[PDB]
Length: 132
Image (tube, rainbow, N blue to C red; front, top):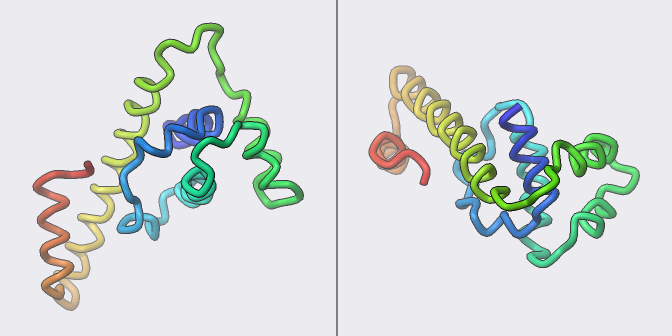
C-alpha cells in the first residue's frame, strides 16, 4: 500500500507530478498499481493546475473510477502541513522498487542473451544512482 498511498496523494495533489521523475524507462514493469499510477501521472502531466475534482471527471465511466474516487479521500489529515514530505517519502519506496526490479530484469537478460550497449549503460546507471 505504499503504491496506493502514492496514488492517493497524487490524486489529492495533482501538482506533485512535478516532483516525479520521468518514468518512461520503468513503466513497463509488472508491479501492481504501477499502471494506475502512470495513467494518473499522465493526466496530471497534461493538466498541471488541475483540481482533484476536475481530475476525477476524466475517469467517468472508466475501469478505475470507483477506486480513484475512494482514494481521493483516503487518509486526508486535518492539517495538510507535511503532505509533500509524505509523498516524496512514499514515492522513493516505489522508485527503489522499480530500480531493483529493472536491475533484476536487465541482469536476467544479460545471463540469457546478453545486453546491447544501451541496456548495459542503463543497467549500470541504475546501480550507480538508483532513481533519481
